[PDB]
Structure formats: C-alpha cells, structure tokens
Length: 10
Length: 102
Image (cartoon, rainbow over all chains, first blue to last red; front, side):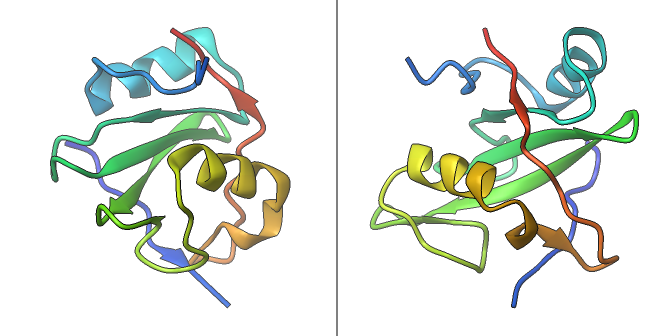
C-alpha cells in the first residue's frame, strides 16, 4: 500500500 | 452516529475518496489492513493524503505514543480539539479539520 507517516510526540 | 468511521474500505479507496469528496483538512477512520484489531486515520493535506496508524490494545487506544484514550471517539475528538499535538518528524502539524462520512 502507501506508507504511514512518522508521528512524533513531546 | 460516529459518521467519520468508514467500516468497509481499503486505504487506497479512502485515499481516492478524500481527493474527490473532501478538501484539505478532511479525514476519516478505517479498520486497518496491516494489523486487524487496530484502526487508521486517513487525512488530507496540501492536495495529498497521509495515513496514521492507531494502536488498539483492548485496554486503550493510542497512536503508538502520545495521549492514551478509553475509546476511539475520545482519541479522534481529542486530536480535533488539540491541533498542535499531532506532528510528524518533519515538523508539520497534521490537522483533523473536517470529518468525511459514509
């Protein structure tokens, strides 16, 4: 499929 | 109601559907092919679509990190109401502005 974004957190 | 949750849709159909039926800021939730049990947020930004994985343990819901929620609605409405908390490595915010419906 298409890729999953790389989420970042504080 | 939970009208933003599309129960019978692939990520590529969702990805097309947002570019036809939605605008930049539109989004939805789906059941996730890659890991049954989980869910996935599919959002539209700058004319293209991003996909976000949502972990469901059974006990709680999360985005493999960040704030943890009892139900999926609590998670979606949280990131709707707190716009800056959903950021990617790049630095860009991912905004859940407008729900897309069945």
